[PDB]
Image (tube, coloured by chain):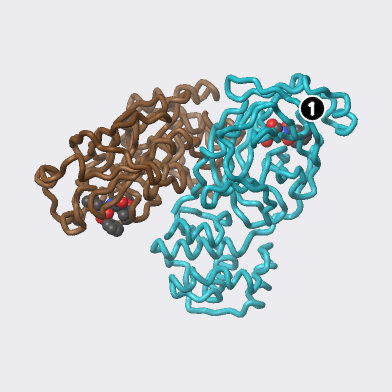
Chain colours: A brown, B cyan
Amino acid sequence: FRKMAFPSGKVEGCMVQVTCGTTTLNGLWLDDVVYCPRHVICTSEDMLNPNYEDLLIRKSNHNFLVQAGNVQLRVIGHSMQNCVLKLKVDTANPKTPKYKFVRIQPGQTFSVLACYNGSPSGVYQCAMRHNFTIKGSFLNGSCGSVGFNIDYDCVSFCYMHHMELPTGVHAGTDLEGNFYGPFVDRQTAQAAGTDTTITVNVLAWLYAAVINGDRWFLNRFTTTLNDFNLVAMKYNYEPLTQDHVDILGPLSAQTGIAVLDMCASLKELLQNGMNGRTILGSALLEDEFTPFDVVRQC
Amino acid sequence: FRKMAFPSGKVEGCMVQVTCGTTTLNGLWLDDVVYCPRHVICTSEDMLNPNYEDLLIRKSNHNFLVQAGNVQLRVIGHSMQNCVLKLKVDTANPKTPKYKFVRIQPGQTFSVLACYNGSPSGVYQCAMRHNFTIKGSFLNGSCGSVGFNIDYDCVSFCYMHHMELPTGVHAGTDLEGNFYGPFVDRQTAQAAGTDTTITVNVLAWLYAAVINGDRWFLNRFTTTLNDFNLVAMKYNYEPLTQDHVDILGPLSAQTGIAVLDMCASLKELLQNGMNGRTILGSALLEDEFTPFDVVRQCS
Ligand SMILES: *[C@H](O)[C@H](C[C@@H]1CCNC1=O)NC(=O)[C@H](CC(C)C)NC(=O)OCc1ccccc1
Ligand SMILES: *[C@H](O)[C@H](C[C@@H]1CCNC1=O)NC(=O)[C@H](CC(C)C)NC(=O)OCc1ccccc1
């Protein structure tokens, strides 16, 4: 098993660069709108304590340089929606895929198309952590890079990149400009909350192990969801939601192992350890493969 | 620090489906030629011990069905180069990127665009191992998927996928149809040579760990190149050459940790183990980042 990104071609065709003054970042060009982080309107000194409403008052359409490659797209309108800027341009993107904007939950994974100066650079899989950070790979100029999932050639955009935290993890918004978690786009010291292990994904990994014949950890016990959740929190594991139980449905059917039976196996693992044994070749439980990632890969 | 693949769009526009009889796989469509694994011409019975030249002479252009999305391409010529089939089509691919065919050496990394039925499915980074296998994620129908690197808009194709070994690792050819390693495109269980670890990559990844604030494995000890190589060979690691030491130059200068000081760190790790500790979130020593991969992602 390995982390596998979605093919990025549909998103590459939507990446542009957006510049205000000397501040440059990436934007997402869908139909005749470009979406980008609103701090493009900041000077480096104003990022310390910006008043975005006041800064935007002083901007006009002609203050924004939007380029596809070195080709300028004329801006014909602008507005701010939460922490993103929406720039109306005079050209509809002929490479616009079928798409939706979605807000994801902790645990969900997505592909990141890392971009610099509007040019795609790399693609990799990320998971949204419990503290609403992602363990990304982002350098200066990466803001406006997006995270996405693809379902039958429809691109679901779920993340746009805005900042790095002091711990080295990253924070951003959905495509409506609403940050994930309690962060703000100000260059002020901020701290990620405590992280937890993503229970639903560890369970998916246990099902993946069972599908491949590694099933020593299956025990004879069951549990209720509430009893499991209370024990799991003592090991810094996330409690399960009803949506989590449901998204494990397909893997449960495939293996014939009830979701709550698997929880009982995981609870035994947490309370007793692995005992010098291994699961899918490792003694560490993996928590960045969703149930969909397991089925998609298998 | 993540395993990052190149953006796959330039390759996606080249993937097509190639069907011969009952067998379906992927092809790579560049200009007016489609490249695909030659075992597409086999039936289920041909695969055990196929005489490919004999099987191919009995095929006509119309035995090959090539679908590009929803459009069928017309095959107007076919030839075989080693384990690769070249189908000439009557249409030039307008999305053909600037490209090169390259044969990579062990330790080099590349991105894989996994495809089924001519449709891209996922992208991930692989490395050519010392025994010329790769640790991929490939299922039935993935043959003809390609591996590649991208440098200033030019796609360097280095791998075409052909087979899975019983150990679960994968084998294939360059785009001239020559296998990496001692493998053959016949339906038999084949073993690889001993899998020696690419030492220069493990050292690059340790430098990546330091650049990202991980230092628990560092020590004050030092080692000569030959004394390090004695321990490396004992643990089935490839010997480090002076060229490897030079290639690690930029990472050494950036961290201030001499290459041989990092070698003494790795030697301790090999002899003492990691003792339950982790490096960049990994419990094992990662060997699929080249020095260039580390410098590119880290800067
Ligand atoms: C946008 O390109 C940039 C992304 C940062 C650059 C370093 N790594 C990243 O992920 N975002 C910012 O610079 C952001 C702007 C504020 C208005 C939110 N500030 C920020 O991330 O502060 C932390 C930081 C800044 C510079 C280097 C390292 C961390
Ligand atoms: C091409 O789509 C396919 C890729 C394999 C399918 C399973 N996972 C893959 O990566 N290639 C083959 O099926 C290949 C056919 C040529 C060698 C003619 N055969 C194969 O990989 O089987 C290897 C094997 C044969 C016998 C015992 C154990 C392994």
**Residue matched to label 1:** B41
Q: Residue at x 44, y 54 (%)?
A: B1
Quadrant observed for ligand 1 in the rendered image: bottom left
- The total number of labels drawn is 1
- Using the image, determine if residue B10 lies above or below residue B46: below
Q: x%, y% of residue B21? A: 76, 19
Q: Looking at the image, which is closer to me, B239 or A74?
A: A74
Q: Quadrant of the C terminus of chain B?
A: bottom left
Q: Is residue A106 visible?
A: yes
Q: Is residue A277 visible?
A: no
Give the residue type that dot 1 points to: Ile
Left or right: A152 in relation to A242:
right
Q: x%, y% of residue A170? A: 32, 49
Q: x%, y% of residue B185? A: 79, 38
Quadrant in the picture for residue A234: top left
Q: Secondary structure at mark 1?
A: helix
Q: Residue at x 75, y 34 (%)?
A: B86
Quadrant in the picture for residue A22: bottom left
